[PDB]
Picture (tube, rainbow over the protein chains, first blue to last red):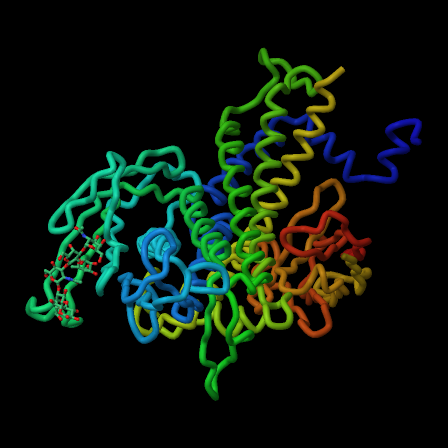
Length: 426
Length: 114
Ligand SMILES: CC(=O)N[C@H]1[C@@H](O[C@H]2[C@@H](O)[C@@H](CO)O[C@@H](O[C@H]3[C@H](O)[C@@H](CO)O[C@@H](O[C@H]4[C@@H](O)[C@@H](CO)O[C@@H](O[C@H]5[C@H](O)[C@@H](O)[C@@H](O)O[C@@H]5CO)[C@@H]4O)[C@@H]3NC(C)=O)[C@@H]2O[C@@H]2O[C@@H](C)[C@@H](O)[C@@H](O)[C@@H]2O)O[C@H](CO)[C@H](O)[C@@H]1O
């Protein structure tokens, strides 16, 4: 228990300095400029922002997980999770085996746990997937630009074969969507905005010219309009993607072969990737927490200069009501940056082990496409991430390494504010 | 979570020094690491950083003079310091980026003439 300040500042000399800076409005104003600039780096910039890279990384890991495993994942049946007798259902723009589609044509077995994925669950997964790929392909916006949209996300699936009822669309009046050329509007909420979808139905006969299934089919097109692309929006989709996979917990089976890296386990149930799925969920959650710091930073601009209220010298004990704002802003920035770092450390294979490590290095953080733009599904996407997972970790690191000064400024600003806040009680 | 710097001393200007930091693997592994210094009357200033892949970057005040490297097998971090001016006199500290909130003891570097 120290009696006085000189004995206290003998030992901790940086504290003397920090007091001198707390009394000097030009020092204070410099700190507040820094907070301006470092804020711009976190939420206004993209490639140089750890926050941006961490969000992108969380999204990419969810997408990549499905790009790795979706082709091996067994799916089938009819509506409401029922088994089917001869129902083939095909989703376009999905990473199937040697294909840009996933066929779900497993008949007879009941969809469910350690079983086929229901078409209901696929649908739910696929929409999240289509939106994420579309956004990745268009490139994500800076964190603060949370009011933009994707003009158009469009995806189709097709149902064929006797008894297949997966393209029957009910609608809220209880009326069926007209199967030949029906077309109807739907809504849902995506971070607090109402998004319309134009859902439409087409029938194509067996004998139609170059219907290559020589089987008649119903095609469902879904056209979403003005889909929000904020972080908070795409994380929620990512969350839906991975939680869908995880709750449905379908059976899957990959054939390993000789040569390549080796899937462990080769077969089982998707939710058996507990370590992988946990981390992806944790990444998503931490990116949500990080993004929520954006508003705290915005609510507390630091661009108004601060002075000795009346042309007379600055008094730290009375002239510094701005300090609670400045403390909260800096703490928000620090928190973003930590969260950002936490996100990369959850998936970075340098700290992984075992089969989880062999998942990320052998599969997730690779791409067998032959480098195409993000969001691209090709006939070699399957069994590899193809979501720039390594490149994204590398950039998160590079962004963090290039934030060394900025991080020190934030700390300094925080202590200065803290110091003022203190003086400011009494 | 431990950070231990060594290697500093007193030198004439134009001198060089090799700073070392043993970091725990929790700190080091898979992390960007970096060097910092704290001169009398100033607050800690970031000096350099290096990614886990070995990409270095530096502060304008030391670019061209200092070199940062990491031995990924020994959880070790180094600062090769050349052409030392009196302005580089400071306690030097090592840490990951973003920082672990408990800093090591640091190592004193003092530069002065004759
Ligand atoms: C109520 C509603 O609107 N829809 C639900 C309904 O869907 C089926 C019904 O509408 C019936 C009414 O007859 O029609 C089915 O669709 C027909 C189309 O009317 C027609 C126009 O192109 O073509 C039929 O295709 C033919 C053709 O592909 C040939 C070529 O090989 O094969 C025919 O079937 C063969 C059969 O496979 C052979 O074994 C054999 O013995 O001969 C016959 C031909 O006599 C094939 O049928 C087409 N039928 C089918 C089964 O595809 C509706 O089927 C749905 O719509 C089509 C276009 C596909 O999407 C199917 O998968 C759909 O199920 O009842 C359903 C329950 O089965 C659903 O609930 C619908 O929502």
